[PDB]
Amino acid sequence: QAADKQLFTLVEWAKRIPHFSELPLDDQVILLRAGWNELLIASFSHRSIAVKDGILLLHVHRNSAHSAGVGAIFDRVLTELVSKMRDMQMDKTELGCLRAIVLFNPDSKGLSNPAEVEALREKVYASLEAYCKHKYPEQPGRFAKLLLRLPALRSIGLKCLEHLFFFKLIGDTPIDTFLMEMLEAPHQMT
Amino acid sequence: DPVTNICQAADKQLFTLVEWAKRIPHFSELPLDDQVILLRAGWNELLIASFSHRSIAVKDGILLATGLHVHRNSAHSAGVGAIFDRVLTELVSKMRDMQMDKTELGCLRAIVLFNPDSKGLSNPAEVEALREKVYASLEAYCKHKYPEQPGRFAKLLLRLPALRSIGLKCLEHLFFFKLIGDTPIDTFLMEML
Amino acid sequence: QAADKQLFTLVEWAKRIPHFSELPLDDQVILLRAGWNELLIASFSHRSIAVKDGILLLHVHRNSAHSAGVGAIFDRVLTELVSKMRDMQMDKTELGCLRAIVLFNPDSKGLSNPAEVEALREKVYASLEAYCKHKYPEQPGRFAKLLLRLPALRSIGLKCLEHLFFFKLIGDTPIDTFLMEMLEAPHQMT
Amino acid sequence: DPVTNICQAADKQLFTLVEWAKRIPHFSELPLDDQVILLRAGWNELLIASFSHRSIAVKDGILLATGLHVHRNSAHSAGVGAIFDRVLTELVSKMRDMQMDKTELGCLRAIVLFNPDSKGLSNPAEVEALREKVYASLEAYCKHKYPEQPGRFAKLLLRLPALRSIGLKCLEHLFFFKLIGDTPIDTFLMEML
């Protein structure tokens, strides 16, 4: 599908993060390949605050998700991220910082140079704490509260990589494989 | 422009599989709803039996039906280098040592395709029979092209548990997507240049 | 639990298999550790033929299993093994041979000496085919039919190692951890 | 007489955990049904945070609360040597490099124990607060015993995603059983002598 359009944006955005383009080329590729998931799930969890139900990717509603056999995980996205995001009114800047934090993930297997990934991460949350403390001084604990959604996004990210999750569509895989099979293409040979 | 390109390969394999199915005797005589059942239930194992036997000509890799010849790689999560390892130890290394021929492989695949356990089947017993005819023929064939090897038939059948195990990890880890997807994604990624 | 009584029988039985005790000591330990599962599931699948519903381990009935949240896998044991076992009237000798075949599993990781595991396996099915052909001559395909339940037992064996399978008992883990917590043991210190 | 012996160790740890919980302030003031929820939801991660920080004194292994010091082993399936590897790379190697103290570990554990996401909770917000008090104190503590390290607090919090990932594989692979069970089972097995 045109889910590489979604893959274009993502890459275009990492490239604009400070210092990401200065990492060894293969490290960048690992980082993106390891984060793309958490990165999307966060992007469309926050975008969803805007509406008042469901996930705004073209706009998913609870009954579909639950009917499509993926209720449990949809409820988790909404309870554990969207709502938490809405209550505390995370702003676009904070989401942007968290996502950067996620990209600069040092425990990613295969990294040629993790110390700097840590180093870059430190740089990003230091600054996020600066932001939080200027912009919302009456909430001393906000910056931790931000970071503490990362385990939630982590376990949710892992749950959207299950094969049953992707086979979300039973009566179209038969329609694919059904059509392929009524093709009378070989009913001639001479 | 990478993703849509991967969907294409997904379409091509699995068009190829379905062609293979149809050229199997009696497979097309079953109700259309059963054909879909057998295929959805079997797709992974029938692909692994292939890329495995194909990857015989290779040393220490997997040959993807399309020239690209793949390997265990550094950033591969525990699970995908693990499947890689099993594929070589339990399927490719064993197929090689016993010099399993393409007739012999065709049979095993056909026996997998006719899976009477497959949930939903309208007539499970008539798949048992098609399964049974296939192995009967496989047996006769072995005792004829390799009569000095009295236990080869069973030895062929006993790659099937492994294949089950392995078929399962691949449907768990999405090994198949990773396979056709890896180069395309790594390569587009060098759009940071 | 006294599921080591079950673990005593199992080991006592491998020891009596021909040639198993002649394998390097650590190989035997691998074989048992890799097969114990398929070995039990087969033993109590065949024992179940005897009754006319459910699993006779102290005798499990379908409603319990389905209520206990483990219906799907219980239905599989019954459809894919017990019933198939009953229809074809597998006998104790054939079960015994299949199980031996399962024990002598050559693709078990860590084996110091797999060639002989293959070798021993060959010896067992050769003989099982002898049996089958003497004892049931009018069924030429029986011996394959036997072996072809091994993928079923394999995938079923794998399904009984899932953690959710073992946590089959919700309202007793709370009773355990609940009791542990009303212990007023430390309400004294001087 | 091995199995019943493993059940014993299961009982001992998880009695030990529950003792730890109760000595946490306010934890016992919550309704009894919530205490059970927090504990069932958290047990794996709270154990991994422990055996990890304990395994600091070790090089390349895991120290099980009871002297027995364990390693990656040949017959270990992909998954269990994999968890082993992660535990050392993402938790033990990192805890070591930053010299995380037992006060600092206690806090992280307490923050895990107070998990407001935990399905079933009767009052989720009053766990948010107990979570919040804990980290507030953790913060103050870091800025005091290590003031030259302005980013340590967060750096502590960011071991938590890893711990989540790893907690999960251990509940998947039954890593915990394997740990206390392995010697006992291998050892009884030498009853073939």
Image (cartoon, coloured by chain):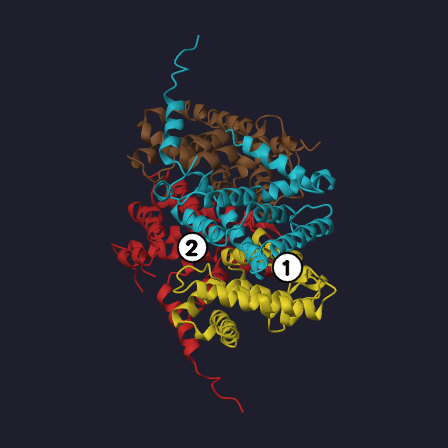
Chain colours: A cyan, B brown, C red, D yellow
Q: Position of residue C112 (x, y in %)?
A: 63, 54
Q: Which residue is mark 1?
A: D154
Q: Is residue B147 left or right of residue D55?
A: left
> Can you tell which of label 1 and label 2 is closer to the viewer?
1
- Does C61 appear above or below B99? below
| Residue at x-position 66% and y-position 35% | B59
Does the rendering let one see residue D72? no
Please state which amino acid type lies under the numbered disc 1. Ala
Does the rendering let one see residue A137? yes
**What whole-number distance in Å separates the C-alpha atoms at marks 1 and 2?**
40 Å
Image quarter where the C terminus of chain B lies is: top right
Q: In which chain is the residue bearing label 1?
A: D
Q: Which residue is mark 2?
A: C160
Q: Nearer the viewer, residue C27 or A120?
A: A120
Q: Nearer the viewer, residue D55 or B129?
A: D55
Q: Nearer the viewer, residue C186 or A185?
A: C186
- Decide: few, some or many residues near mark 2? Use Cα within 10 Å; few <14, some 14-19, many ≥20: some
Tell me the SS state at disc 1: helix
- Does B134 appear above or below C44? above
Q: In which chain is the residue bearing label 2?
A: C
Q: Is residue C82 left or right of residue A111?
A: left
| Residue at x-position 51% and y-position 59% | D174
